[PDB]
Length: 169
Ligand SMILES: *[C@@H](Cc1nccs1)C(=O)N1CCN(c2nc(OC[C@@]34CCCN3C[C@H](F)C4)nc3c(F)c(-c4cc(O)cc5ccc(F)c(C#C)c45)ncc23)CC1
Ligand SMILES: Nc1nc2c(ncn2[C@@H]2O[C@H](COP(=O)(O)OP(=O)(O)O)[C@@H](O)[C@H]2O)c(=O)[nH]1
Ligand SMILES: [Mg+2]
Image 1 (cartoon, rainbow, N blue to C red):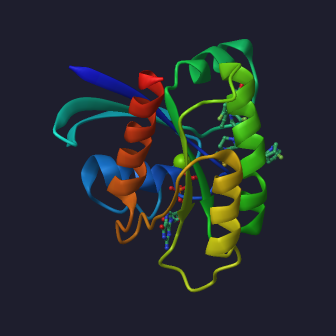
Image 2 (image 1 turned 30 degrees about the vertical axis):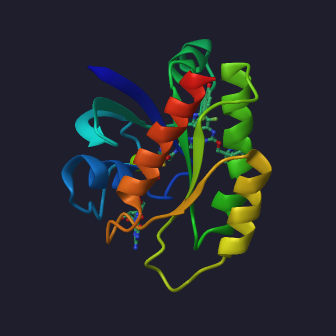
């Protein structure tokens, strides 16, 4: 069976855990310990192909050991998550893209920009800004809400389609 290694990255509090649990369980978690970093597996059918998605939900203290670089290097695709009500989380996206570029030693790594918490009215990052950033990186932009499940399957399934496009090159 085909297997895809996906990694969910972004600032603390953006909804990485909430998005992962929404994809895995179809339930919204109000509280998920921000120190818990773990991987989950879900069997899905995407465009007729059965596959196992192994999703690493990053968390815990920010550190950069060589062991952590090697663990991130195993990721085939990354969701760059920011929250639409947190400008600092959007400003931090460049850091996450640079760290992916550094450990993968590549300019062409499958990624999707995800603007989470789209259910909140307290927007501080406009959709146009996020679309321009994703255009500058050559990647898709998807608006999500882990609370209502808006865009959740689209974010993960779009990342799987980007990994498929990369494996074809
Ligand atoms: C919060 C978890 C909490 N623990 C306790 C209380 S809350 C959470 O979800 N986190 C914490 C932050 N993590 C993390 N943070 C960053 O950068 C954060 C910023 C903001 C403070 C200063 N620092 C630099 C920038 F200004 C942004 N970067 C992380 C990071 F890059 C990696 C990591 C590590 C290595 O070795 C390689 C690597 C390669 C690709 C990657 F995508 C990432 C990632 C992510 C890599 N790990 C954690 C980082 C995690 C989330
Ligand atoms: N309204 C709303 N709250 C969310 C959403 N996603 C996450 N949250 C909340 O934001 C907080 C941080 O979410 P969490 O998944 O722990 O973020 P992480 O640190 O990136 O793993 C929690 O209180 C979640 O319930 C979302 O899309 N909408
Ligand atoms: Mg978390």
